[PDB]
Image (cartoon, rainbow over the protein chains, first blue to last red):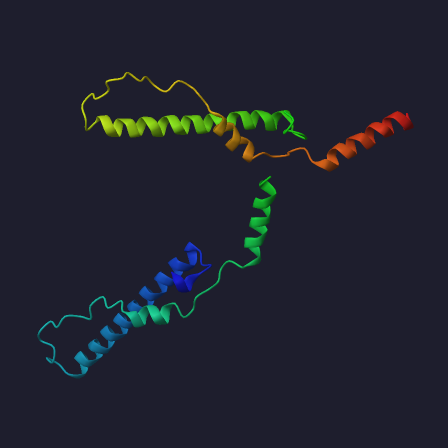
Length: 89
Length: 91
């Protein structure tokens, strides 16, 4: 929250959503690599080894919120506070 | 009245209505507090107090007039006076 001064709800939701996209990409690429190595080496994975967990990790969020967008500008706040001061009498 | 210079009738009605909101706020909060007490101590009132009779104090009016709006502007009166003078002179 401290780093995200001046960020609306939409930006926070987008930041949260991007990390899940990265996690899905990682999981799918790992699954495809595992499937390829199953083709290369038959019977090498007779036992159903557990797939990568939902490792929504610090690095995922770090790379996701690198593209942090200031959706709302700064001049809007002065406009709204000027209108409020006009209301205040 | 001497402190309401440049005030419209609608603004004065709004100011009068404002204090009743504070009165209702006070009454509801006080009765909620009171029922918070006597739901723990069963019927402990040696002196009999009814629902607080409407007794809106000077503090409510002071708070209400602290937030007053001059809806009529200082240029509108000048424009109306100019139009009145135009009516007097032209026709």
